[PDB]
Image (cartoon, rainbow, N blue to C red; front, side, top):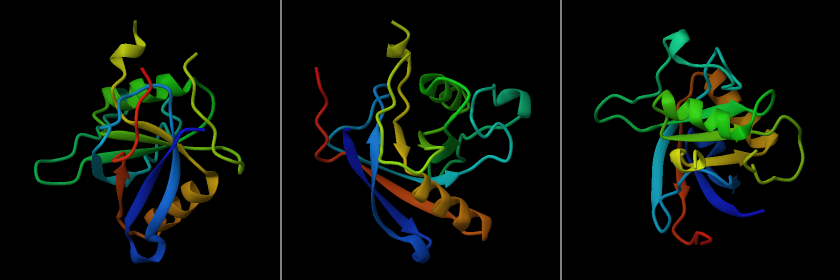
Length: 153
C-alpha cells in the first residue's frame, strides 16, 4: 500500500500527522505539497451521482483554500467518485473507508488519463475524527505531502 503523509493543521484538537493511501488514478503534485480545507457534503456523500443536480460546487473562492472533499466509500467505483468530484471543482478527494481496517489501495476498474484530481483513501478512524470536527463547527485544514513520493513509470 503506497502511502503519503497527511498533516491536519486545524482544529488544534486533531492536529497532527496521519497516513493516507494514494489511489491508482489522479495526479499528486509529486515532490510538492497541497494545502486545502476539508468539506463533507450533506448530500451525495458517496459521490456516485452528479453534484451539479444538487447545485453543489467545491470550487473555492479566490484567496480561500482549495477544497478537499471527504467522500464515503461504497456503491460505485473509486475512479467514478474522483471523476465526479473533479467535475464539481474539488482540488482533491479523500475517500473515507467504510470499515475500520488497514489502508487499502484504490484501484481502477485512455479515460484514466482524464482523472487528475489527487485521490487518496483514509481510514474510517481518521474520517470519523474529521467528521466530528466539522460537526462541531470547526474548519478542518490539511496539507497533503508528496515531497518524497516518487511515481511509477
